[PDB]
Every structure is written in structure tokens, then in C-alpha cells.
Image: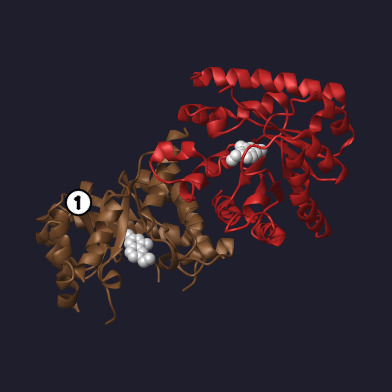
Chain colours: A brown, B red
């Protein structure tokens, strides 16, 4: 029942020049987003990724906008280390110990996401997820990163396997991750394919299956939420809180 | 938390509206009904009221003329029909048509039609409304007494108690005060226990939702869905909505998520 901070998804490439992604990043802030999750990915490339970030990064910092960057490459990550973005989203969970001490000299909060790319007993995935967090958080702490800087993401959708039951189990049991490590947790359900396998609808185009899962996560204590339609979630969270 | 029926709103007057001519497209309303049903609607809430207040005998026979083809066609396909009208002459036409529900936003205040309502097998949607700056607490108390007096006067005439569905009213029907709508939304389970009757919640696209967020809720679904979700988990028996598919798809997520 805690107020969740919204993460606005802005993809730099599919929106673009830089201005179409910039104006998409301020319209979401004008809609109730606390942090803008910047993504700039194409096909097949470190300089190409960074070149699209620099104009959007410092433009949002010129207006005091908290920025999250979705990158799994350490060279792109070390760039975000010294640009001093407020968040750095890694869908791989920092598996390369090269930049470990590099992440300790910084202060940007780290987001530790877990995935399991093939046979899914849905609870066995949860247990190994508990052990994955226990080993990766410790090694990050041993490298100098403060424990108060890690945010856990249990993964969702195709990051948990083609089985929709796996994503349902984690959506019901993510409070257990909250109290086992005493740390914040973000849930990302927006337009993920497994929502269509439950309702039989055209995902990526239907907001309501998506909205129902984000309110459920908010009502169970999710600290952060990652979505596309921000003004829809912002109004869903305003109604949900005022309604008791 | 449990079951919930969905009322599909079909404004026959709106589906036959004015793009440069009025109330001759009697098939758009019929297609809007059959559409909403394959989106997950349980009952079709037909509404053929005039665009502006009309209280003559012509507006009566005009309301039946807009309901007569839509009611008939939906009957041939086994569709639960609910008529959204507050006129006694229109309601008597719905009784002889064997319509499933009669949705009255005035709470049936005319005793002349009580005789016709007793013989009917249709269910009744008794709605409560407000006088016209009343404190939200006193609106709830007067609503309780209003249901208590009107339910008795209906069973006195011969309407079996179990056919009465209670609607507390929402938004402008409770006043321009948003907290009055919030109080009813978070305290309506007290209605189902005091009267042991079903309760219908109708929040779809009401102005008070915009006063809480600050967005145009008349054409948007997110605040309508958030409020419709809360009433579902709180045990609302029926749900009157516009976007049936978005609510039906939403109910399929909460049922899987538990
Ligand atoms: N933290 C987090 N980030 C993501 N980035 C991209 C995508 C692709 O949908 N998913 C996610 C996600 O599920 N969680
Ligand atoms: N049963 C019921 N019917 C309504 N009809 C029209 C309108 C106006 O939107 N409201 C309602 C309502 O709140 N409850």
C-alpha cells in the first residue's frame, strides 16, 4: 500500500532526431513520471549507443529530471557512471566484475534484474532467483557498492520463460523478496506478452490488462513501476490511493 | 473477490445521434449491443432518453419507438435486456416486453406503477440521488433511510424483496463534492449487509474521477478502470460500464492474479 515511483519508458531510436525523444521524455514527466528510463537500442555497437544518449541525458539534467538508463554493456555503463545519471537499469544484473569497483566510486542506484532464458517448474525458478540475489548482492557489497543502492527486479514476461504461470507466481510472491533482503523492488509488466495469454487480447495495444497488473503490484508494496502509458498509471494510482 | 455481472451501456439515442439528422439509424444501436456482448457484457443497459428534458406524451411514445426495434432484436438472440428509463409509461412497456431489468435513476417514486411492477418478473435497479452543500457523512445516512423506506413501499405493493438491486448513486448524483463519491465507494459493502440485497456500482466516465487526478475522464478509461477495479474487489454485484472489453479483460487479470 506504499506509493510507487513511476519509471517512464522512452526509446531514443524508435522515437527519432533527439527532439522527438526529448519531448516524449518531458510529456511523461508532465504526466506523473518520477524517473525516465532511457533506452537506445538497435540491431547488431558501443559508440552508436552512447552517441544517442549524450544529447538526451544532459537535456533532462538541465531540467532536474531523474534519469534511468537501460544498458547491459559495461562500456556504456561506465559512461553512465560519470554522466551521473540517477539510475542504471541492467537486465543482466552486472555479471562482469570488471566494472564492480567502477560502480562503487559512483552513487547512482543500481537495479539488479534476474532472468532465466529451458524447462520451468515455476517455484524452482523462484528459489534459484532467491539464491541469485543472495550471491550477486553480496559480491556487489564486497566490491564497495553500498547495499542501500541496489534495487531488485525479479524479471517478467519472456524474461521468466514462455510459461505465463511463472510470471503470475512472481507477481504474487515478490513481497517475499522485499522482506528477505530488506530492499526495494521494481515490477515491469507494461504490454508484456504473457498478459495476452491470460485474457486472449491483442497485447502491446490493450492498456487494460496492463493497468490491472500495475495496480495489483502497487497494492502489494512495489516500490517502483516501469510502464509505457504513464498518465494512465498515474491516474490509476491516484484513484487507488484515495479510494482507501 | 468473487463474481460480478457487467452492464453494457447502449445509449440508443447516442447510437442514432446527430451527424446531420436524428434517430433514424436504428441498426447502429443494435450492432453496438451485439458487439458489447462478445466483449464480455452480461446485460445490455438500453437507454433511449431524449437528448434534452422532454416531459410530454410525445417523448414517451418516442422513447418506446427507439426501444421497440432494439428490444425485439436482442430478444431473438437470447440477450439480457435492461432498460434505463425513469418514466412510468415507458416502464410499463418494458413489463409487457418481458425485459430482464428496469433501471430507474429516480428510485421508483410514483405509486401508480407499483401494481404493474408486482406482476412483473423483472428485477429492479433502485437508485438513490441527492436533493441538489451537504456533508458527505449526512449523504450516506439519508441514503440508508431512503432505501429503507422505498424497499418497504415496494414490498407493500407486491414486489418480492429479492428482485430489488440497490444503486447508491455516483458522482453528480451525490453532489459536486468528490469526497461524497469516495465515501460511498469505500463504504458501499455496508449496503449489502444491512438490506441483504445486491448492489450495483456505476462509476464509468463520471466527472468526480477527473477532480481526483486532473485529466479528461469523459474520453479516457484509466481512472474509470481504477475505480471499477476497486468496487470489484470490494464485492460489487453489478458493474455498469462503457468500455466493457477493457473491464472484462481487467477482471480476467485479477482473477488469475488472485
Ligand atoms: N528493469 C526491467 N527493464 C526492462 N527493460 C526492457 C524490457 C523489455 O520489455 N523489459 C524490462 C523489464 O522487464 N524490467
Ligand atoms: N443504474 C444507474 N444508471 C445510470 N444511468 C445513467 C447515469 C448517468 O451517467 N448514471 C447511472 C447510474 O449511476 N446508475
Label tally: 1
- Residue B117 position in % (x across, y down): 84, 33
Nearest the viewer among A90 and B233 is: B233
Task: Write the residue at 68% across / 30% down.
Answer: B106
Task: Write the residue at 67% across / 17% down.
Answer: B145
Task: Write the residue at 17% across / 69% down.
Answer: A76
Image quadrant, ligand 2 = top right
- Residue A149 position in % (x across, y down): 21, 50
- Residue A2 position in % (x across, y down): 37, 39
Label 1: few (<14), some or many (≥20) within 10 Å? many
Residue A113 in view (yes/no): no
Q: Quadrant of residue A54?
A: bottom left
Q: Residue furthest right?
A: B119
Residue A50 in view (yes/no): yes
Q: Is residue B106 left or right of residue A89?
A: right
Nearest the viewer among B186 and B60 is: B60
Nearest the viewer among B89 and B214 is: B89
Parent chain of label 1: A
Q: Residue furthest bottom?
A: A44
Amino acid at each position: 500500500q506504499g506509493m510507487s515511483k513511476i519509471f517512464g519508458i522512452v526509446n531514443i531510436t524508435t522515437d527519432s532526431d533527439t527532439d522527438k525523444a526529448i519531448e516524449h521524455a518531458l510529456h511523461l514527466v508532465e504526466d506523473g513520471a518520477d524517473v525516465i528510463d532511457l533506452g537506445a537500442a538497435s540491431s547488431n555497437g558501443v559508440v552508436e549507443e552512447i552517441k544517442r544518449l549524450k544529447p538526451v541525458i544532459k537535456a533532462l539534467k538541465e531540467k532536474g529530471i531523474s534519469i534511468s538508463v537501460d544498458t547491459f554493456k559495461p562500456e556504456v555503463q561506465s559512461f553512465c557512471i560519470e554522466q551521473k545519471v540517477d539510475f542504471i537499469n541492467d537486465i543482466q544484473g552486472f555479471p562482469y566484475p570488471e566494472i564492480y569497483s567502477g560502480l562503487a566510486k559512483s552513487d547512482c542506484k543500481l537495479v539488479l534484474m534476474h532472468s532465466v532464458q529451458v524447462e520451468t517448474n515455476p517455484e524452482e525458478v523462484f528459489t534459484s532467483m532467491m539464491e541469485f540475489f543472495k550471491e550477486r548482492i553480496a559480491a556487489l557489497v564486497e566490491a564497495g557498492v553500498k547495499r542501500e543502492r541496489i534495487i531488485l527486479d525479479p524479471g517478467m514476461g519472456f524474461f521468466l520463460g514462455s510459461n505465463p504461470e511463472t510470471s503470475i507466481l512472481v507477481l504474487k510472491r515478490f513481497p517475499e523478496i522485499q522482506e528477505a533482503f530488506n530492499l526495494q523492488v521494481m515490477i515491469a509488466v507494461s504490454r508484456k506478452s504473457f498478459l495476452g495469454k491470460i485474457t486472449g487480447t491483442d497485447v502491446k495495444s490493450r492498456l487494460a490488462p496492463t493497468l490491472a497488473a500495475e495496480m495489483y503490484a502497487y497494492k502489494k508494496g512495489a516500490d517502483y513501476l516501469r510502464t509505457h502509458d504513464v498518465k494512465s498509471l498515474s491516474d490509476a494510482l491516484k484513484i487507488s490511493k484515495a479510494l482507501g
